[PDB]
Image (cartoon, coloured by chain):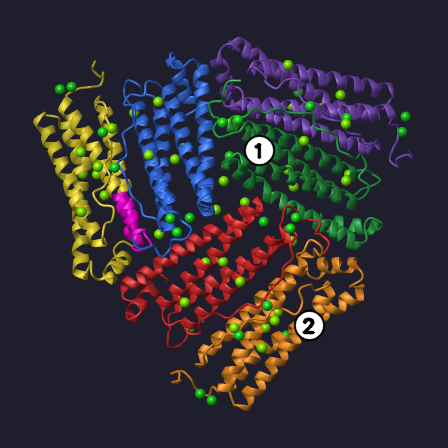
Chain colours: A yellow, B blue, C red, D green, E orange, F purple
Amino acid sequence: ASTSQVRQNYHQDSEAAINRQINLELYASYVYLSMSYYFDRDDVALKNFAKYFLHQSHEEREHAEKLMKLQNQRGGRIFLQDIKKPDCDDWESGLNAMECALHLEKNVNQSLLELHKLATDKNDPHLCDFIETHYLNEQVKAIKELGDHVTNLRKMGAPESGLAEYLFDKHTLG
Amino acid sequence: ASTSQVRQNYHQDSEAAINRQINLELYASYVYLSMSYYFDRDDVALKNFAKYFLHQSHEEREHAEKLMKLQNQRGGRIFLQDIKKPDCDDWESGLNAMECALHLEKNVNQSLLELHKLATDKNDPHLCDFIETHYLNEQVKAIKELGDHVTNLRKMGAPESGLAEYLFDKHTLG
Amino acid sequence: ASTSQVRQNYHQDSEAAINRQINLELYASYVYLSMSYYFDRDDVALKNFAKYFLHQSHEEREHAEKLMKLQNQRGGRIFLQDIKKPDCDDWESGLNAMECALHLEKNVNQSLLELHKLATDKNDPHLCDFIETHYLNEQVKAIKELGDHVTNLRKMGAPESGLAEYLFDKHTLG
Amino acid sequence: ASTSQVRQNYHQDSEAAINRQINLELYASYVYLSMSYYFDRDDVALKNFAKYFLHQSHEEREHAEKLMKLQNQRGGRIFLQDIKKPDCDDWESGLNAMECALHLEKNVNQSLLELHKLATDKNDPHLCDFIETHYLNEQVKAIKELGDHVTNLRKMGAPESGLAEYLFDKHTLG
Amino acid sequence: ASTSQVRQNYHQDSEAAINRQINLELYASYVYLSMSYYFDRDDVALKNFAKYFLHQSHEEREHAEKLMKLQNQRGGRIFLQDIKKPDCDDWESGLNAMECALHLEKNVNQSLLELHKLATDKNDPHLCDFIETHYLNEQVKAIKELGDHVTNLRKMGAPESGLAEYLFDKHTLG
Amino acid sequence: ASTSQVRQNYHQDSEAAINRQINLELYASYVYLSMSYYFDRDDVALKNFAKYFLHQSHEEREHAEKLMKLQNQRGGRIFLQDIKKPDCDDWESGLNAMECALHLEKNVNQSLLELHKLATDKNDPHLCDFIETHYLNEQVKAIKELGDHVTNLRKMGAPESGLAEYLFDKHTLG
Ligand SMILES: [Cl-]
Ligand SMILES: [Cl-]
Ligand SMILES: [Cl-]
Ligand SMILES: [Cl-]
Ligand SMILES: [Cl-]
Ligand SMILES: [Cl-]
Ligand SMILES: [Cl-]
Ligand SMILES: [Cl-]
Ligand SMILES: [Cl-]
Ligand SMILES: [Cl-]
Ligand SMILES: [Cl-]
Ligand SMILES: [Cl-]
Ligand SMILES: [Cl-]
Ligand SMILES: [Cl-]
Ligand SMILES: [Cl-]
Ligand SMILES: [Cl-]
Ligand SMILES: [Cl-]
Ligand SMILES: [Cl-]
Ligand SMILES: [Cl-]
Ligand SMILES: [Cl-]
Ligand SMILES: [Cl-]
Ligand SMILES: [Cl-]
Ligand SMILES: [Cl-]
Ligand SMILES: [Cl-]
Ligand SMILES: [Mg+2]
Ligand SMILES: [Mg+2]
Ligand SMILES: [Mg+2]
Ligand SMILES: [Mg+2]
Ligand SMILES: [Mg+2]
Ligand SMILES: [Mg+2]
Ligand SMILES: [Mg+2]
Ligand SMILES: [Mg+2]
Ligand SMILES: [Mg+2]
Ligand SMILES: [Mg+2]
Ligand SMILES: [Mg+2]
Ligand SMILES: [Mg+2]
Ligand SMILES: [Mg+2]
Ligand SMILES: [Mg+2]
Ligand SMILES: [Mg+2]
Ligand SMILES: [Mg+2]
Ligand SMILES: [Mg+2]
Ligand SMILES: [Mg+2]
Ligand SMILES: [Mg+2]
Ligand SMILES: [Mg+2]
Ligand SMILES: [Mg+2]
Ligand SMILES: [Mg+2]
Ligand SMILES: [Mg+2]
Ligand SMILES: [Mg+2]
Ligand SMILES: [Mg+2]
Ligand SMILES: [Mg+2]
Ligand SMILES: [Mg+2]
Ligand SMILES: [Mg+2]
Ligand SMILES: [Mg+2]
Ligand SMILES: [Mg+2]
Ligand SMILES: [Mg+2]
Ligand SMILES: [Mg+2]
Ligand SMILES: [Mg+2]
Ligand SMILES: [Mg+2]
Ligand SMILES: [Mg+2]
Ligand SMILES: [Mg+2]
Ligand SMILES: [Mg+2]
Ligand SMILES: [Mg+2]
Ligand SMILES: [Mg+2]
Ligand SMILES: [Mg+2]
Ligand SMILES: [Mg+2]
């Protein structure tokens, strides 16, 4: 119960929202992990898709860690939840994985936007700045990159052209 | 259904056991993550406990990844499950965290030993070698290190001596 | 007849099996040699297929040499046999060569697995360790790589697309 | 009585066997020490035989130390015994010393093989791996080297040719 | 049937003769391989004989490869045959191995001379130049070196003097 | 029986005394070896005590070797005896180990002093100089260092303070 000695201008609702966001970032890490190893299957075998999604997975773990650090910086208390498995076991194709990643990042961005709204409603400028500085432009860049990737794959003839996915793997992700 | 072109001498039971082990390693990663940020709380404030457990968390993620790679190398199919949250939100003390980590690593080791027994019963020497080479001695070393740590903390007067935990933090984990 | 001064715990059946395995490795070297120069024909002209299979040929000669060294280390006696010519003179296509290499490596792996079973039945842990350390994971990696290659070529449109085989030659084997 | 906190899957019989093996390695160190200084006598005066056996003596001390470390890693308890003096005070000749070293290393290897059998019967894969990784191939290499040395000395005309032992000292051990 | 686009002034008899020569070079590689590991036996133990013959074995594999490349350069088609095992399993002595190698190289040289005669009869100056440039002087040098070696071993008292073979191993092959 | 060609002014009693001293130095090496691994136990876990005593163990082996060399330099003949196991299996504490080491080094010093008395009574100045130069001041320094260590541990509150032994381990032995 008793307060943290550091706590100031940090609403309990913001504290809870940061714990939800921690879960979401870990969930995103897990989705990209799954995607990565899909492309490492002997019957998929797109090694640069695999590295690309692994890198993205590790990023998301870093995003989670930074929110954990924030929780403590502000005197909130971290409460972890189960990290749900991804929706898919088999991601179908390079294009479909990229489409799923785009939708994931748009979902993560919507959560961060709700979090910023809350921080604004509770007049927490430090939390607003945090989210703006470390998260919002990362999301906009990730979303733009994924859209670019989907566009290229589509134009190249994916998913039906295995050639298209192979060449994208070498030229864009390589 | 149809076979993987790479698959040879890889029993379905071993395939399932590797998927269980993947979950366990990710679970271990999560426990150490939680422990790490506990020591980063302003009311705990043992920064080298925090770094030590973070490093251990990242290790475990690497151990999971290597099993995922193995699954694919052998032509098995990765099936992920929810990563359960840790048993504890509050780890009590440096000593109690170390005790919990020891019990975690002994549990992980017991799983790997059951996995090796299975691999032996199914006459899978490649899988036996894998487990021996990459996992079993890591576990024995981790277990020994954690026991050493618990011993020192106990001898120093933890958990009642906050001095003991502070000085261990600086001299052993620092 | 009279024993080797070094010989210990080395069954005559293991000695014979190692001589068979020596022949098999040299045979594998010969198959890859043949494949290599097929891709060097003026009417095939895929120079990176050619280098890839030449490298694999030299590897296999090294694998044979290490078994010869082992035979002597254990006090067995090397008995060489004719190295049979490969099954094919003309390997048809990049894809078909890769398919044949996959089947070759799976055959070599099955032989090594039978050899390990024998070594296990004769309670020869040094020989078990030898095979595990120097051979079994090499086979699993070779098999996985070849499967990956076959998958890519298939997805790209080989063997009918001469473009697919040309581009694979440059991007994967180059 | 009470258990070690680290102990897992480590049979008391294996614990005792490791203590016996520790004694044997120290015993081997002592035999090579004695051999070394024999060749340093003014009436023997083969300085490279002396260095060769001293190096081998120090190796064996390292092999003992690694088993001591293992005992502790696994939660067993080290119990030392007297290190018996070697069988011989006077080793007769370079050839006879080499012959005695060959028989010593074959004895040490037989002990390690019995130890591996025990570890296998008690389903201790970590201990099996330990012995395989750190000991069995060292023994096979040592045995092969000693056999090679005995062969050369014999072919050269030792022990009757003092010239043979002198020249072996310079060309093989030098 | 249909011609190679590159083929010019390349008689079918020369094409067949190059395929025979390819087999012979691989056969020579195999003889030297066998010789090499004979000297690696614990009861022979002449390590520089072993390295010398291994080097010669690898050379011969290179000589085969260059003929394979030639076949393709000229638009002929490679047809491989079984590589026969060597005549001997046990090479008796350093001197006898050297004598056998001399006879092998003289046989290989006689084949190359017949090949040059054919190339001359078919007015193939490119093939004549090839053989002259890459093969004939190599043979003359190899033959001279082997004769020199046999002479020295004979003068030193081989094969009865094990000392002679030991010292040759160190001073000439070392 | 017959004399060594090198022997001069070297009494048989001195020869025997040097053989006894060789045994004592090896015995000291063994005591420190045992002490070292005691501190490596998971329930003791003082790693710098362990390194300190291991270093001391290796020193003593060097002291033995130098006496063996001396025996031969003077034309005496080395006669080895069993190296007795240490008095203790369990050394109780850092303080008690240090106390036992102090008593060991004082015993070794008393032996060397008796040896010097003998060398003096037999008018062997070379042996007197040997002992003075290589042994007596080493003993005085070792004894002083061990006394210093015991004093510090005692003042710090050992053996009851596990904190004291931990901090000594880091600051003095570290
Ligand atoms: Cl607040
Ligand atoms: Cl609030
Ligand atoms: Cl939950
Ligand atoms: Cl930007
Ligand atoms: Cl299977
Ligand atoms: Cl199955
Ligand atoms: Cl689940
Ligand atoms: Cl280790
Ligand atoms: Cl045997
Ligand atoms: Cl047998
Ligand atoms: Cl045959
Ligand atoms: Cl691997
Ligand atoms: Cl146990
Ligand atoms: Cl037990
Ligand atoms: Cl005893
Ligand atoms: Cl080896
Ligand atoms: Cl023509
Ligand atoms: Cl023609
Ligand atoms: Cl044939
Ligand atoms: Cl010349
Ligand atoms: Cl005298
Ligand atoms: Cl006297
Ligand atoms: Cl005795
Ligand atoms: Cl001083
Ligand atoms: Mg959520
Ligand atoms: Mg891969
Ligand atoms: Mg990202
Ligand atoms: Mg994120
Ligand atoms: Mg669910
Ligand atoms: Mg989706
Ligand atoms: Mg910014
Ligand atoms: Mg589980
Ligand atoms: Mg902090
Ligand atoms: Mg770890
Ligand atoms: Mg793990
Ligand atoms: Mg739950
Ligand atoms: Mg717990
Ligand atoms: Mg290992
Ligand atoms: Mg065969
Ligand atoms: Mg070419
Ligand atoms: Mg290969
Ligand atoms: Mg092979
Ligand atoms: Mg045939
Ligand atoms: Mg085929
Ligand atoms: Mg390995
Ligand atoms: Mg014994
Ligand atoms: Mg000397
Ligand atoms: Mg050795
Ligand atoms: Mg040893
Ligand atoms: Mg006795
Ligand atoms: Mg003997
Ligand atoms: Mg090894
Ligand atoms: Mg022929
Ligand atoms: Mg050798
Ligand atoms: Mg040559
Ligand atoms: Mg040739
Ligand atoms: Mg035949
Ligand atoms: Mg012959
Ligand atoms: Mg020339
Ligand atoms: Mg004594
Ligand atoms: Mg330790
Ligand atoms: Mg000392
Ligand atoms: Mg001493
Ligand atoms: Mg004592
Ligand atoms: Mg002095």
Chain ID for label 1? D
| Residue B19, above or below C103 | above
Q: Residue at x 78, y 67 (%)?
A: E154
Side of D101 where A78 appears, left or right: left
Range of residues picked out in magenta: A32-56
Q: Residue at x 65, y 74 (%)?
A: E105
Residue B105 visible in this rendered orientation of the protein: yes
Q: Are labels 1 and 2 assigned to the same chain?
A: no
The C terminus of chain B: image quadrant: top left
Q: CA distance from mark 1 to mark 2?
A: 51 Å
Tell whether position C159 is magenta: no
Residue F105 location in percent, x, y?
68, 18
Q: Which residue is mark 1?
A: D66
View extreme (left): residue: A121
Circles 1 and 2, Cβ within 8 Å, touching? The answer is no
Does the residue tagged 1 have its C-beta within 8 Å of any atom of ligand 8? no
Residue F31 location in percent, x, y?
65, 22
Q: Residue at x 44, y 30 (%)?
A: B142
Tell whether position A44 is magenta: yes
Q: Which residue is mark 2?
A: E102
Residue placed most toward the observer, F21 or C40 = C40
Side of C58 where A84 appears, left or right: left
